[PDB]
Every structure is written in structure tokens, then in C-alpha cells.
Length: 282
Length: 282
Ligand SMILES: [Mn+2]
Ligand SMILES: [Mn+2]
Ligand SMILES: [Mn+2]
Ligand SMILES: [Mn+2]
Ligand SMILES: [Mn+2]
Ligand SMILES: [Mn+2]
Image (tube, rainbow over all chains, first blue to last red; front, top):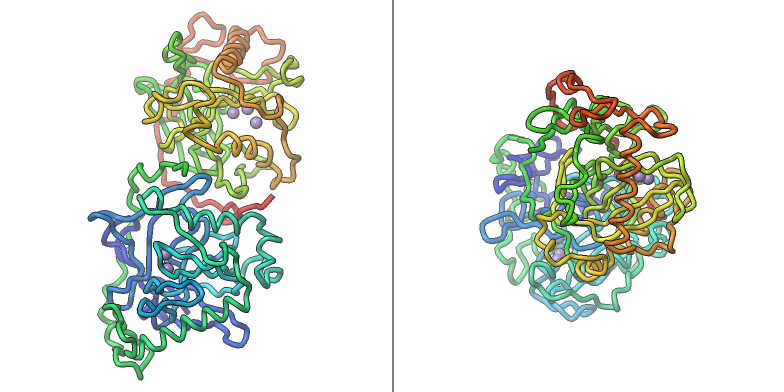
């Protein structure tokens, strides 16, 4: 059973969310199995950012057990700006654990090195997710985002508990039940960083969302890269903390890491600067 | 100076927000001057619904001093649904006090009776407003919405404190600085009740946003409709509570109504049913 342990108040620099397995903190990056059901390709998706929020929360590569923490910018919290007609993130945003976009080699489909992070997932169900949630999802497709020149695949998925889950089985079903969502997805990822002064992003395949079969192949590739990484066999792990508490045959295995985590110290959400309210027309 | 007096928790039936003038409650409908600066065309806007929220809050016509409360439908709190790509209301939504869409006469521009409510205002500034807030705005234009067959003008305005206020003078400036907003506004008002099982709404003039001069004329007409109403001269005031504490020459003036209001009893927001998360693709 997966639960969360929150340190601090949301929207503060001290805020951390560890994922617990039977009450014990585990690595959100390495200890959560990629598959909830291997035979049926049902994946475990770690949610970082709830739909319509702005905080750039992420499984941290630099801290032990990789808790979800907010990224920083010039000493303060990092937030994505609202880009008309969108409000914050337009998907329950997260990643699949036990995956890695290898930054050491150039990926052929995109002709660029990976972004050094677990593969990303866009969960399109109706219910807004919570930070640290581990939900079970079906893969529907994938888009080849080049984010600031780096391979940055976006898997399109749906929570198996969603009322529409039974009807969503491949990429064509997203346009059938969520018309316009894919085009908006393409747009959002192209322009979301422009308010921060970054250039517009680009997609391979002219922004085409590849199907489930394709998605599964890429997911497997990123899972294989993580297998090499966690074994300590990457040519360069980029200082990522590979500490884990469920993989005994790995060099960085350490059960005590779980017991070192401070107890929950939940505090109510802290105020977010009103500047984040701003709607950008770009 | 205008402040707010909150009773109960947001998202509850007991929730009320009274507008105070120098600490004393006044009618949000009748006691707040329409004009902050008449000759410069600056108006006082009463905010009911902050941008990106769902609750259908409104200056209530049938309670003394007309506090803002949440509208209901079949005994349950009324919430507007999310219509892709929109999240809740896409503007700081409110009304102009001392105005009334006369339901007793068919309006010639729209060929329909008014909706019995003060004239509506869509404030397009960057900052998210707060319920019960009294802000000064400039009128830029107006759209003739026919909401469920009733005259329902929507004034397009900007908070004078907005960084872009000095550059926004007429309706054309909205397209320049807020490209796509007018089109999305037309769409929003046409489709927002479809998730509730209601027909698509319609606009007069093919949805054209009339200019500042046109907007001023309609605002003034609704102000005149309210002058007849407050004087007790309407053929049918529809049970509207006309009690006021600042208009001594009106029949319903009452210098005791203000002190009859209970003191603030602000509570934390109550939870909103998770079904309100749902994004409708209609
Ligand atoms: Mn990521
Ligand atoms: Mn990225
Ligand atoms: Mn990424
Ligand atoms: Mn109204
Ligand atoms: Mn209406
Ligand atoms: Mn109205």
C-alpha cells in the first residue's frame, strides 16, 4: 500500500513528499515497480504535479530516497506561468519510476541526448491527482518532445479507475473522447517556457502522438536505461542518488535509508506570490 | 474604504459575504455607487467570482443588504463545470451595483426581457480577485449574451490598477494585448451550461464585442432601470430586497439594517466535491 509522508507546508522551500510502502519511506525513483501488472501493461505512475497547479514539483535526483520537492529559481520556488488559454499544468503530471532518459547517448528518434530524468507521464483522467500519489495507469500513446534540445518523451496515459478507462485503449481514443486535448498538449509543451525567456520547444514527428505499441517500446527502452543506471553500470550517473531500500543486489542498496527519514510534519499550504496569477498571451 | 465581512465557510450554504463601508455593512446591490469617477468613466465593480473558480456566487437579491452567497439548484450548491480548454470562470466575474437588467420589458437590441440581475462585468486583469472585493474599473466594450433566452449583457472591463490599464482604452485594445480572449469569452458563455444539460447559449450581433461608447450606453440604461426600481416604481420588483442604508430619499431606506447584521465568523474553506474536477470536452 502506497501512502505519503509530508514534511513542511506546500509552497515552501522545506516542503518534501516521500512515498511510503507499508508506512516505510522508499525511493520514489527506484523502489516503486514500473509495472503494477506486467502482463496487462498497467504501470505505476508517480504523480508530481496536480492538474491546474503551477509549482514545478519533481522526484529529486539529488536527495536520498528521491522525495518530491519543488524546484528553485534564484533562491525562490519555481513555478510555471499561466499561458493562455491554459491554467498551470493541463494534465496530472508525473513520471514512471525505474526509468531514465539516458543523457549520455543520443536517442535516434529525436537525435538528442535524454534529459537525465525518469520518463514523463501525462495522466488525462477527470480527477485531479495529489502530489506523491502512486496511481495505476494504462498507456495510450507518446509524444516526442525536445525540451530545450533534450529528448523528453511524454507518455499519454489514463488512471484505470477513471470512468472512461474501459473505452480508452489506444491513442486514437484520446481525440475521440477528449477532442482538442492532444493539440493543446502539443501547444502547451511548445510554449510554456517562453514567459521564462526560453525559446519555443519542438517535437519530432511534427508533433504526432505515436500509438500504444510505440509508447511501450520507448518505455521499455527507458526502463532498460534505468536498469543499467541502478546497477552502477552507467558511464556517468550524473551524481544521481541511487540509494534504495528494495533492491538488495544493487551497489547502493541500504535499508537504513528508510529509517533515517524524519517523521511527517504536515503544515497547511503556504501562500503563493500573486505574480503567479498572471496570464501570458504568447 | 470598502472591506468584507465573511459569515461561515466558503463552499457551504451558510456562507455569506457582506460588503462593509468604514466597517459597517451596506447593500452590495444598492449602496455602492456605480461611479467611482463618472466623467472619467471609472466604475466600482463588485467581484463575486474569482478567476479559475467554479462556485456560482452572487449578490443575492432576496436577503437584506444583499450579501454574496452561493446560488443553489435543487437544494444543492451550484458550481459551474470545467469546459475544455477552460477552468471554471475565465475572468474575475462580478457586476456593477445600482444597475438592473429589467425583466419586465423586452430589450430591443436582444428582443428579450432582462435577467433580473445587476449588469455583469468581466474584469480581465492579471491579478485574481476576491469575493466581495470592490475594485475600480474601466469599461472597454460589451457583448450581448442571451442566457437561456434572457438579456444578459457582459461588460468587458479592466482594473485601473492593472499594469496594462493605461494601454487599454477601447475594445480593439483587448484583442491586441489579450489575443484570443474575446473569442474564448464568446465560446465560454455559449457552452458553459451544456454540461448541466442546458442548450448552447447565443449572442446578438453574431457575438460582436461592441465598443466602449456602446458599453457606456447600456450600463447607463441599466443604471436608469435601477433608479426606477430603488424608488419603488417598477411594475414588478420580483421580491428583490430593496433595503439600503445610504439612500435616505428612497422608501426602503433603513438605518437599522446594518447593525442587524451578525459579526464576522470566517471559517476555512469547506471541501468541494471531487466531481467538480471533471473537464468536459463539449
Ligand atoms: Mn519529469
Ligand atoms: Mn522537460
Ligand atoms: Mn523530462
Ligand atoms: Mn450576475
Ligand atoms: Mn446569466
Ligand atoms: Mn446576468
